[PDB]
Image (cartoon, rainbow, N blue to C red):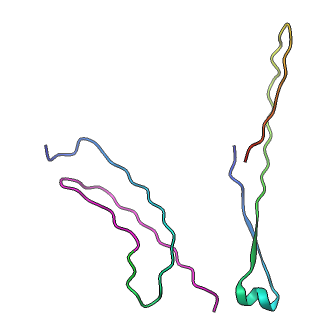
Amino acid sequence: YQTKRNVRREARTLMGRFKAGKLAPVMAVPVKGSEGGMLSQSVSFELDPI
Amino acid sequence: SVVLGRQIIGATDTAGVEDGVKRSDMAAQLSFTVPIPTTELGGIIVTFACI
């Protein structure tokens, strides 16, 4: 039973603001037992006017 | 169907530069050419445009 037969799919797009100098978490993808595959994440950056 | 494009126009005055004022413009074009179906009693062709 611990062998791949079916597949899951997740697509989460999020937006927010995090203060500089802080290790800010952005996303948390769950992985259950006997699972694997490819993970692709992308994050944009845009600072306030200086 | 089509997804609207975007063009950004930014302010240049002192207030706009400091605050960062900008505008978004959205436009699109759609057209089709299809034959009219011949019928004995005719009909009405109604067009729709939804955003």
Q: In the image, what residue occupies the spot 75% across and 88% down?
A: B17
- The residue range painted magenta reads A26-50
Viewer-proximal residue among B13 and A3: B13
Horizontal relation, residue B51 to residue A41: left or right: right
Q: Is residue A25 magenta?
A: no
Where does residue B23 sit, x and y in percent of width and height? 76, 72
Q: Total of numbered circles in the picture?
A: 0
Q: Position of residue A30 (x, y in %)?
A: 29, 61
Placement of A31 over or under A49, stated as above or below? above
Determine whether, in the image, residue A22 is placed left or right of residue B39.
left
Residue at point 14%, 47% (across, down):
A2
**Image-quadrant location for residue A1:** top left
Of all residues shown, which one is farthest toward the left? A1
**What residue is shown at x 75% (from left), y 76% (from top)?**
B22
Quarter-of-image position of residue B7: bottom right
Q: Is residue A8 above or below residue B36?
A: below
Q: Is residue A11 left or right of residue B48?
A: left
Q: Nearer the viewer, residue A32 or A2?
A: A32
Give the overall secondary structure of the magenta segment: loop
Q: Where A16 falls versus B28 (above or below)?
A: below
Give the quarter of the figure containing the C terminus of chain A.
bottom right
Left/right of residue A28 with respect to residue A1 in the rendered view: right
What residue appears at the point 31 percent right and 45 percent down from the top-left corner?
A7
Q: Name the foreground residue: A34 vs A26.
A: A26
- Could you tell me residue A14's position as x and y percent? 48, 66
- Taking the magenta stretch, the answer to whether it contains residue A33 is yes
- Name of the residue lying farthest toward the top: B40
